Length: 30
Image (cartoon, rainbow, N blue to C red):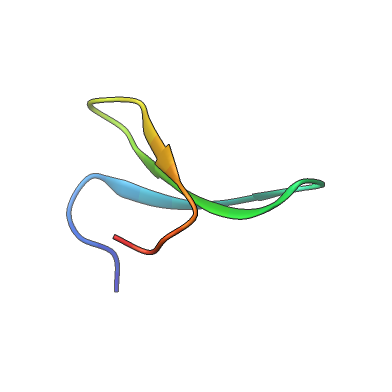
């Protein structure tokens, strides 16, 4: 249950999180 505007991303590198308006990207769930 991500807050508004956030996505969970997975790719070869791992699973991390992405804030669409700001480009903020981080490991920790928001």
